[PDB]
Structure formats: structure tokens, C-alpha cells
Length: 21
Image (cartoon, rainbow, N blue to C red; front, side):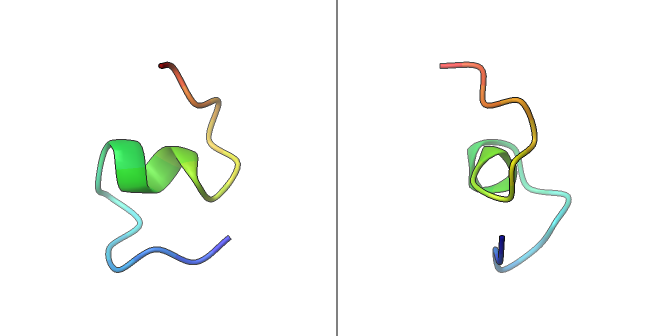
């Protein structure tokens, strides 16, 4: 879990945020 900005969208799914492909 570590993205540039936690508010991003797909970069946010990488931190375990229910990725919705």
C-alpha cells in the first residue's frame, strides 16, 4: 500500500481499496 496520492483513483486501488477494474 503506497501510492503518490492516496486520493488518486486507480493508483488508489493498489493500496487495497477494492480495485474495480
